[PDB]
Image 1 (cartoon, rainbow, N blue to C red):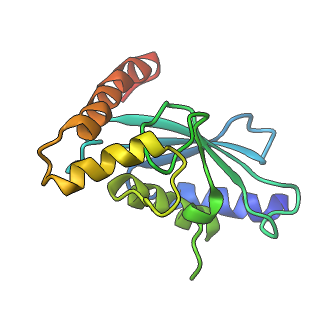
Image 2: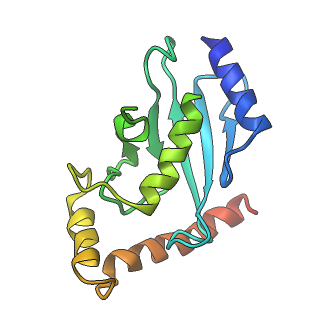
Image 3: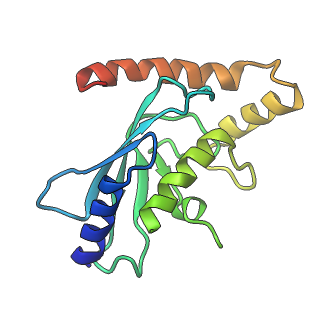
Length: 157
């Protein structure tokens, strides 16, 4: 419903999740949303500004949205296209709020059960088998974090 999405949008603009700003792409189209994501201050994402998109079906909330990062992200659970499978964002237990909360969660601790990016996953593990001594997985996050300044000059804050 347009009502469900109108209610969800308004509810997320009235009580934001800290580090997430949600807007409509075209204010005349409730089915496509843009999400701004500000990296949490004590992770390797801190200072980063990431951009992602949400697409909802015409039968929402019966059917879940699609999530995809616009920013390229090196991550076990993110595809090169930017896609994250919705089931890892909306796990077995309002919808978009919980989705946003999984994003913080997934950014902080990857899920190596069955990874989208195996190279990222093999690297993330190296980062664990050594107590942070192999900085490579951590290095790419940093590079990606500071590359996002360019995006956040193109618009800002």
